[PDB]
Image (cartoon, rainbow, N blue to C red):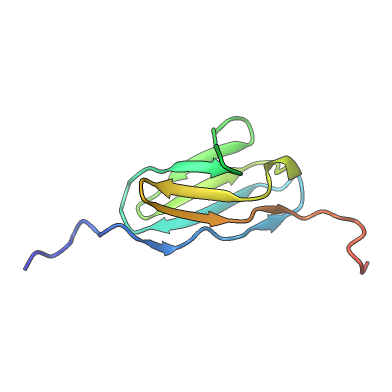
Length: 102
């Protein structure tokens, strides 16, 4: 038959909800079944532009999102979208001193 060497597009590993304290560098990944394709990144409904803190990378299947020196302003939700297929994770900056248990 026709062996799909071009792996049919799918969201195998969805975006993962990463939580880290400010100052840390983050790199959230999403495994898109299609090798070496690009996707629009979104942060809280906005097109995520790789400026300053933000860096966007793409591997074979997985798409990576880097935030160096993360801020609570860069938190909430990230969404990786490729035309139809989309994915999302809650990025939380780890943070509150009064966490009800020092």
